[PDB]
Image (cartoon, rainbow over all chains, first blue to last red):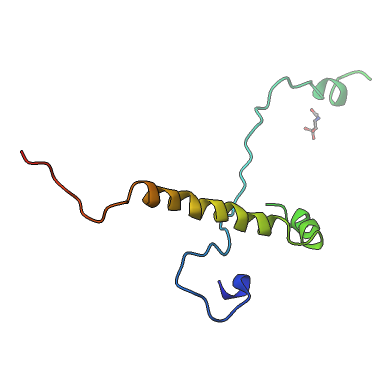
Length: 49
Length: 49
Ligand SMILES: *[C@@H]1O[C@H](CO)[C@@H](O)[C@H](O)[C@H]1NC(C)=O
């Protein structure tokens, strides 16, 4: 409170000096679901090219 | 909660920190209206049964 009040003699009272929040740590991301596969085996391992 | 965005605020000065005091400035006196319109008596009276 002293830094924000710019004084060393603070009076008896309530003083809001800063704010706090919880910082995320892992940040998980699970959107996808593997589907609609287009065969690359039909162009890589086809018998005749 | 953007670090680089906050840097843009420092060079812009002390606007929002000033109004935060103003908002608390109205808030503290907001409750001050209550005791001067309700707490006009220091004796709490209970009605007889
Ligand atoms: C084709 O077969 C080879 C050998 O098994 C394999 O390494 C390759 O990944 C295959 N290609 C595809 C996309 O099926």
